[PDB]
Image 1: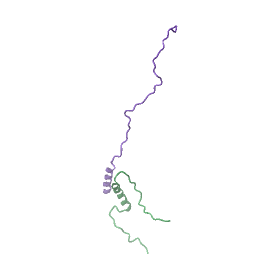
Image 2: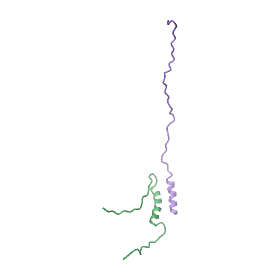
Image 3: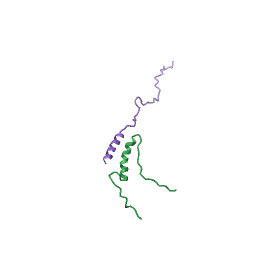
Image 4: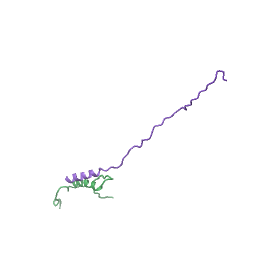
Length: 51
Length: 50
């Protein structure tokens, strides 16, 4: 029983080893939008007689 | 066809860590299964017939 407790403690510290890290690479990314209409700014001014 | 097999059981082993450290844990369980963990002597001289 004493040996079982000693072997258990040793195995516990052997299992305390890291494997990897996982994360997300999202900094710098932004969401795009869509503009449906071209913003022209033209008006036509004509005289009453059309001259 | 016939065959003889030793059945000592199945013992899971984890990869990536020390095998000897896991073996020691399984050693005590195997000793308990075989009945050799505590001090003992064998009395098998009366297990016979004629």
